[PDB]
Figure 1 (tube, one colour):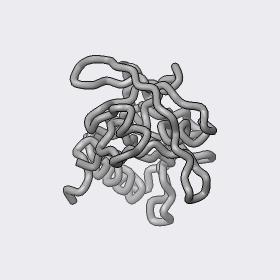
Figure 2 (tube, rainbow, N blue to C red; figure 1 turned 180 degrees about the horizontal axis):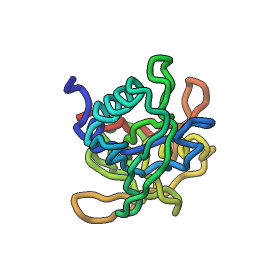
Figure 3 (cartoon, rainbow, N blue to C red; figure 1 turned 30 degrees about the vertical axis):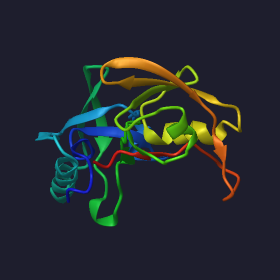
Length: 180
């Protein structure tokens, strides 16, 4: 389907690693870009899926996962998962903190944030996933938060205050993820 941005199909980039997962056991990290597995090239998530299935069918028990971390290539040894039993690697796709839309009136519509902005840092701690953004907006507990952002080629800074909600008293700021 076309209802997701291209980067969520290719290349394959880990956003989260699950506890007790195969991926966790072997030290895969958010940021890693899976490029090959065994002798199958992994350009897209379907490539990864197919690769894992094929190996699992051939009854192959272990193989080499190739990934790129910090522009350099690591080789890792993996247990081929039980595909038919729905056993997975344990990786979720990365959704970057590029802003897709802003809600009229929100602490982020106020403080100037625009669609297309990329959020590289909040309170001097670097981030690379959307859930890390939200994760900090939540834990913020009222006390406003600094965002280091990349707009149109330049860094900028915005400092905004999380609005507590008449829902569950949870702090939001009013940014939608980019689905375009």
